[PDB]
Image: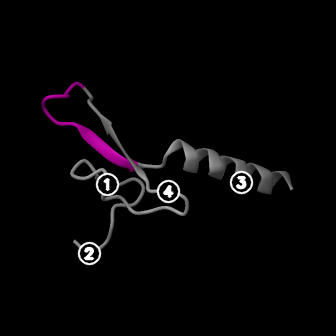
Amino acid sequence: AKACTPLLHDCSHDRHSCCRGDMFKYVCDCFYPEGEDKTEVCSCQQPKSHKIAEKIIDKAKTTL
């Protein structure tokens, strides 16, 4: 109960609990695998901004 909820972690209990990012805060994704009113599975993920950013960075780096 000291650390935070980084990428690939349980955030179903809190979507705004995930760790902060360099540009923005991570995003908590949710899914209902045949159980929307039973048990929703959520996990910490990165926003479209962070994703795209990394992609470009990595691409250029490997391109240079």
Tell me what residue is drawn at x 56 percent, y 50 percent: 50
Q: Is residue 24 magenta?
A: no
Q: 10 Å neighbourhood of mark 1: few (<14), some, or many (≥20)?
A: some
Q: Is residue 38 magenta?
A: yes
Mark sitting earlier along the chain (2/4): 2
Above/below status of 7 relative to 33: below
Give how far apart the Cα atoms at labels 2 and 4 are.
Answer: 21 Å
Mark sitting earlier along the chain (3/1): 1
Give x and y (percent) for residue 33: 27, 29
Q: 10 Å neighbourhood of mark 2: few (<14), some, or many (≥20)?
A: few
Name the residue type under label 2: Lys
User: Is disc 2 in contact with disc 3, using a CB cutoff of under 8 Å?
Assistant: no
Name the residue type under label 4: Phe
Name the residue type under label 1: His
Mark sitting earlier along the chain (3/4): 4
Name the residue type under label 3: Ile
- Residue at the disc numbered 1: 16
- Residue at the disc numbered 4: 24
Front label number (3 vs 1): 1
Front label number (2 vs 1): 1
Q: Which residues are magenta?
A: 34-44
Give how far apart the Cα atoms at labels 1 and 4 are.
Answer: 12 Å
- Residue at the disc numbered 2: 2
* Picture disc at residue 57: 3
Give SS at disc 4.
Answer: loop
Residue sitting nearer the eye, 13 or 8? 13
Residue sitting nearer the eye, 51 or 10? 51
User: Is disc 2 in contact with disc 4, using a CB cutoff of under 8 Å?
Assistant: no
Residue sitting nearer the eye, 52 or 40? 52
Give x and y (percent) for residue 23: 55, 59
Give SS at disc 3.
Answer: helix
